[PDB]
Length: 506
Ligand SMILES: O=c1ccn([C@@H]2O[C@H](COP(=O)(O)OP(=O)(O)O)[C@@H](O)[C@H]2O)c(=O)[nH]1
Ligand SMILES: CC(=O)N[C@@H]1[C@@H](O)[C@H](O)[C@@H](CO)O[C@H]1O
Image 1 (spheres, helix red, strand yellow):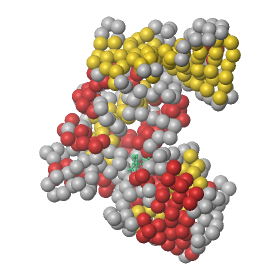
Image 2 (cartoon, helix red, strand yellow; image 1 turned 60 degrees about the vertical axis):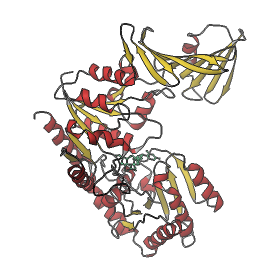
Image 3 (spheres, rainbow, N blue to C red; image 1 turned 60 degrees about the horizontal axis):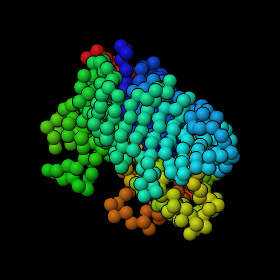
Image 4 (cartoon, helix red, strand yellow; image 1 turned 180 degrees about the vertical axis):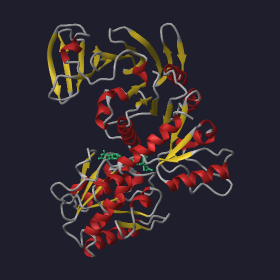
């Protein structure tokens, strides 16, 4: 490549990803619009799914995607198109019968000692994402497929448990490119046939060098656990930007003489002299971080404010908004405190029996949330919707609720106001203070460090009730759209263009 390329580095991606991954997807949308060459690199081993299925889901174009382990081969990022028949060709013939159970297809043979389990992309299609080969009860090999087999895993029995010892990655023609020798989940040795790498760091270094980075390239680092030093070192011949996503230090641990950074930034902040610029989503975080660099460190890095999201256009309700309908959208994670919202809604429902509350997202808090709902017999008006595509969802509702105690930005807050939702949330930095004008487009609720649950639920309940009882909904929605005009894609393109124009040239 001769053209400027923007390389973006993250660990992983899933069906129900965090805002970090969605922010990357927003950024990809911007780079496409600016007709700029970009790559989004993921460094995690992802085998449970075809990585292309995940990236396409979130909206990356296939040619914007680099997967670390695939990169050294000539197999392109692609959807799974291998069939059951294609799969069975890798294993010996003579099928006796099958068993199907959803996506799990087990193919039995007359050789009673062997069977193949296929894991289908779609229960009602014959596309096979990966397959498992079992001999006399023992798992021996797993193959992984896109348009051909790109990876095999090799297993041997120990105490009757299958132990992974080797992973091999292939080229299109079926020849192996490299083997990873495994030890209890650690990728210890990467054997490239004519050379060898010891440890993932060395492997990632080789990857970085394989990019042939030019001075006019930009490396943007989103997440970096395990690989920071190698990325930092190899990015010096290009330009290096670090995106700060969440709150970046611990207030409770910090005092006049000592600061405790967020673990995901400690490395980057310690070595800020190696970073060309940091990116933050709000000016308040910008100023906070700048001050802390001056107060606690010997660095004075460049820090630019670029929102991680933008709104293409405001979205109007297409068929109207259900009366008294409430929405929240997040990972079901402790730091979002959706349980406080559920209890608040149960309470407000005493005064407004028409209230409903839909909860979008996935996460380990689902068990607690179901328990609270069951305990109050609230199933008919409070529901978990799962992780969904939200673009058409928000404008079907009246008001958005958040009990998150901290947001670097909060993409669902931006998305919510872009669809004309008033917001009710805690008066906490940074996102809530960016997106909520108390009394104009919703309410900011004072937060306390002791976090008394009874007080919290009473406050949210009171505020929800007040919005409806004082007839504030029309005015607040209108004000949300007004705030949202400050977060439109047109503005953001210019911010990126400007930043890109400054890394290109000087
Ligand atoms: O059911 C859901 C819930 C969330 N999201 C997306 O996940 C991202 C969450 O980002 P945010 O900044 O709100 O929270 P984070 O997960 O970063 O704390 C947003 O872009 C949402 O649109 C989604 O697509 N479907
Ligand atoms: C809890 C928290 O701070 N989450 C931040 C979010 O506010 C921000 O929108 C996103 C994308 O930058 O990074 C997140 O993970």
